[PDB]
Image (cartoon, coloured by chain):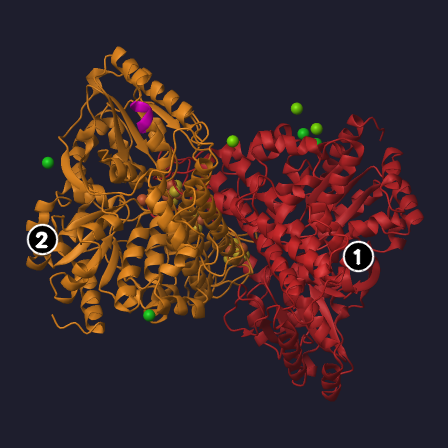
Chain colours: A red, B orange
Amino acid sequence: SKTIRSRSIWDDAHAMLEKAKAEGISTVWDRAAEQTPACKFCELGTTCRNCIMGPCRIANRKDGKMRLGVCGADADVIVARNFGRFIAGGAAGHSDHGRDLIETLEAVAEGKAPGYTIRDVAKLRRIAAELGVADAATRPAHDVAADLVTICYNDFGSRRNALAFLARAPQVRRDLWQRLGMTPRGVDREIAEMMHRTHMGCDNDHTSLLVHAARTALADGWGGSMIGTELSDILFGTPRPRQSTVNLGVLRKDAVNILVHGHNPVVSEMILAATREPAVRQAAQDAGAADINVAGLCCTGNELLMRQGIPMAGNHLMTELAIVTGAADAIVADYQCIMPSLVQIAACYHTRFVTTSPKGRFTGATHVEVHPHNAQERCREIVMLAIDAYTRRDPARVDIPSQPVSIMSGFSNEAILEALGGTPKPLIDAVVAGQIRGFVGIVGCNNPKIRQDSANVTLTRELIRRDIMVLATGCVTTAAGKAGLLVPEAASKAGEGLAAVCRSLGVPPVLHMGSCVDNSRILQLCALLATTLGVDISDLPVGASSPEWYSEKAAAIAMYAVASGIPTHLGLPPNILGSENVTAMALHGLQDVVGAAFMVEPDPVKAADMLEAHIVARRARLGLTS
Amino acid sequence: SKTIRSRSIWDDAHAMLEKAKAEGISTVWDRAAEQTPACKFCELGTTCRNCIMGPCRIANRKDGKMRLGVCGADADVIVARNFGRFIAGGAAGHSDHGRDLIETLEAVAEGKAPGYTIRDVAKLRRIAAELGVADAATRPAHDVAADLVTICYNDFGSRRNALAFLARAPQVRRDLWQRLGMTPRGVDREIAEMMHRTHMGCDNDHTSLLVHAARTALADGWGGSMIGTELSDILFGTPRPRQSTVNLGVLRKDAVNILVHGHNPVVSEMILAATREPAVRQAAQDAGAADINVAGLCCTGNELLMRQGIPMAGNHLMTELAIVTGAADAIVADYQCIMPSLVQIAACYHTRFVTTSPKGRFTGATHVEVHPHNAQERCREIVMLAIDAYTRRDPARVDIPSQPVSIMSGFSNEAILEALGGTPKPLIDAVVAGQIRGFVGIVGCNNPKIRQDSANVTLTRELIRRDIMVLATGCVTTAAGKAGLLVPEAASKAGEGLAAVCRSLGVPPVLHMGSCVDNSRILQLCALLATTLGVDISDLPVGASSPEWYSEKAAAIAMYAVASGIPTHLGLPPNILGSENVTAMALHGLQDVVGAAFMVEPDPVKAADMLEAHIVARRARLGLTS
Ligand code: SF4
Ligand code: SF4
Ligand code: FES
Ligand SMILES: [Cl-]
Ligand SMILES: [Cl-]
Ligand SMILES: [Cl-]
Ligand SMILES: [Cl-]
Ligand SMILES: [Fe+3]
Ligand SMILES: [Fe+3]
Ligand SMILES: [Mg+2]
Ligand SMILES: [Mg+2]
Ligand SMILES: [Mg+2]
């Protein structure tokens, strides 16, 4: 229908929306329509439920009533506190993610994690040395891992003046954060401090609240997320370029299909390993299947793509539709971004919905809890449940639409530097020559308010045509992949300068740099280029964009990008427009404080113009043309 | 006047409400009226703003529209997540408070805190030995302090299996918490995990969410709060019984009046010291003042009262009225429960409003930031500001409405045990013999929804009449004090059994045990009684009540009491009634899980009946026949 066509740009999404219609299954778009119009105070941010003197709403009434909350707080404070707690929730998602990796590395170092290993010993020794572990180059690997675990845990404590990985940022940027009171000190400490500041009668100054929101977000980007990324590479391997495929057509009628969903590779890597064990494969063959087929959703999907080349079935708004194919024999979830509607949709089929984390509980799910000491045994058990469920698939309701689209994944910073010959000199040369005018990270989600992937795809296409290389993470990965942008032959979609550089290196014009925690790789790349050139991150020809964001996590990434000096575009506004002062600080005031600001623009072509304009202005201050 | 009499039971409040109305000053009661009726969804908890797929509201309609959020979350999940973040904000308040005490003790141990010292060396050595410091009885005090600092900081890290002070709880309770997954592990860690669990698509099971809310609150009561109480006693002295006074009449027309407000004695103790320096007093005399008079508000007032006998001007809803006397020359604020309306009310007079914490910023305040290394110099500057403001005081606008009333304060557990002769045996014997039926801690706030202190005082009177001894903390202290119940002669208002015990010890029937963090003293006392008798806390004839609560901190206290086995009454419901399942768990289901539950009851006589009924049942669980 016209409604279905308006919900997504993709053929596979349309086919499943028609099928969900015929089967009477409601989707995220139907619930979004039920929640429109939204509450006007909630959307503006001018409501507070932080104590039971309230709840309070701030209105503009002719009688002048409801200008203040019961405690006396005005719209500036109420909006800034709501936004601070919103950012803290996003930082906490990445923080707990990093913490789980520390605990997994510790279990490996203690010999208490069967099936887990140090997959990248060289990176372990390099990271440990960088952070100050003595004799990291020569001591037994597990001893070095134990000392690296201690350093990472200290960043989740309360005794540091600055996070360990902050040393990567250029000195000028660290000096600025120190003057501003933005230096992140402890990953959990800043989240806790934000929750204290936002209690009634604590922080009642919108500027101070926004400064701490920046500090809390920096504790994610340079702490929780960066620890998460670097330890994931140590446990599961540093990504290198590899071929794979994307879209609902990666599911196979002839195989047992297991979709992995959520964020943490500690689970999805062990599910993949279980499906490769000979006795498990034989059980699938006895059931009538040709093979076992693992396919990724969302960030845990990105993790398996980066390190194992596992095909990705879809991003956020495809998740329900992947079930509607009728071919999902099990969905294995850990935590974050897993819509609870998936439990009810899975119950419309034979599909098993399996939870694995004590943090990600879903009423009605089959819970098989996974920890380092038992993952090998439990993941074997979960794959066996998938195989059993396959025997009851209803073949009449199977509709796998579309043929999969080829992609190239695996662009860690290590992989980029290797393609360049071991130094950033050829990339710097390309930027100085104007062949590559700048870089934009396009990150984040889908949102049913925006036709799915329409802005993600349009923005990526516009930027590469203007010789701006795109670094893609998170759910943008699937959009760029389905648009044919993630392969070396996509150099033909870029402008003449970027196409030539890509062809000379053999890489695509859009580089998949990983999951949402892997936005930390973009910070590390920026820091390296700034330190190499002797400038600040706020001087580099860079930008960031989340055209279709929805999550608290995406807002935390955008805040840490801005506070690190990267101009950051959002397709939709956070719930802050009820305060002109908070809004003006996010869109304009921060520009002169931290060197960058937020932009809000729902037209992806106009967003391309704004990101390009910031890049051009930064090129001028480096003394470059174009 | 009938409206004014409806707002408070107290003459001093009545007098200042009349003065405020005559002067056009808006109070918390006026703003509460403007915010009534409240938003129905906010009040019920059936609204969510945790992502920009929303905001979402949940209705209960026969057609089933707006039954779910855009992500699919139902009322049970939305309500439980909202209550979880509510609890996390309260735990965070106490956590940051405890953290600041660690940092101050560290500064003393390093020799970098002029004017601070270890005031109670004997308690330092006992606490350090209790928590495992080697040779705590003989090593240099600064070495012992440094080792205790390290233990406390490790509780603010991510490597423990259980908080250090949790060892005080009886083994049976520790075993239950461990099996339930409720054991608190790290003070900041549990807060961060709550914020992770409540992100879209993480924890989507209301039972799981409430269990982690209990774990988060327990990390406060046995962690942040207990650390704060024990280190405050080490740095500033263990409280011992002493007489003082209460009400607005503690302000003096002929003196420079400095009100300390907020929570942290690290500031208020140094303000007090500054007012005693000879040169500062000479400056006050040069201005025409007879004295410099410090008086307390809210929790920091409680702290100075407990350790220094400093008179208390009022509790939460008295704070605006204290400025309306016209005699407040400065308000010196740190953080928490400081209504921002105080800045505007101060600007109606000569009063200086001074902020001292980087966490407690108020737009328009005079900021003089205080840290251990500079407090001596900065507090002197703050007192000079107050003296200058005194020279600007308009005598025509002064109305100090009452004469103060005597109270006894200082009942730390050390003081109680000393009064009992060194052991708890005389108290246990009185309970066994039925002279004291049980104990109730009455804790927490005021709330403009309830006539001020009406339920606090009526519940206190009802309980002592039934031979139930009351332990009072927080803003209830001022209520019981103004009612005349904090003195030994108030035994005449108790039942025959309690009166006889009180008279035999020379103590009041209502024992002031300190500020809100000092509810940790009640946990310690319950744990000692249960350990001595060989039972659980959930077997003791104890209860807790906050008849007039408002804050996230009060909800966290109630939750940690319930989770520790103490039945807890609340005068008003949290914003949870939109979920019958969450409400039933809070009020009934938790009884099976943790051995105690919440009660919600606005009639304080009925609340007394309910607390007494739990006490009767616990006496039967102990086999008592008296
Ligand atoms: S913190 Fe202030 S604005 Fe928020 S609900 Fe409480 S009284 Fe209202
Ligand atoms: S988390 Fe779910 S219920 Fe909450 S605002 Fe987002 S879509 Fe709505
Ligand atoms: S639902 Fe209560 S203000 Fe939006
Ligand atoms: Cl800058
Ligand atoms: Cl810029
Ligand atoms: Cl008296
Ligand atoms: Cl029990
Ligand atoms: Fe994501
Ligand atoms: Fe309090
Ligand atoms: Mg500062
Ligand atoms: Mg400038
Ligand atoms: Mg600039």
- Image vertical order of residue B218 relative to residue B232, above or below: below
| Residue A77: percent from left, percent from top | 45, 36
Hey, which quadrant is residue A161 in on the image?
top right
Q: Secondary structure at mark 1?
A: loop
Q: Secondary structure at mark 2?
A: helix
Quadrant, the C terminus of chain A: top right
Say if disc 2 is inside 8 Å of ligand 6: no
Left or right of B73? Residue A598 is right
Left or right of A320? Residue B402 is left
Type of secondary structure dominating the magenta stretch: helix
Q: Which residue is mark 1?
A: A410
Q: Are labels 2 and 1 assigned to the same chain? A: no
Q: Callout 2 environment at 10 Å: few (<14), some (14 to 19), or many (20+)? A: few
Q: Which chain is mark 1 on?
A: A
Counting labels gives: 2
Q: Nearer the viewer, residue A117 or A456?
A: A117
Q: Callout 1 environment at 10 Å: few (<14), some (14 to 19), or many (20+)? A: many
Left or right of B306? Residue B160 is right
| Residue A146: percent from left, percent from top | 65, 57
Hey, which quadrant is residue A534 in on the image?
top right
Bounds of the magenta span?
A: B272-276
Which mark is on residue B504? Answer: 2
| Residue A329 can be seen in this image | yes
- Image vertical order of residue B574 relative to residue B613, above or below: above
**Does B275 lie within the magenta span?**
yes
Instruction: Return the residue found at the far top.
Output: B286
Quadrant, the N terminus of chain A: bottom right
Say if disc 1 is inside 8 Å of ligand 8: no
| Residue A400: percent from left, percent from top | 74, 73
Discs 2/1, front: 2
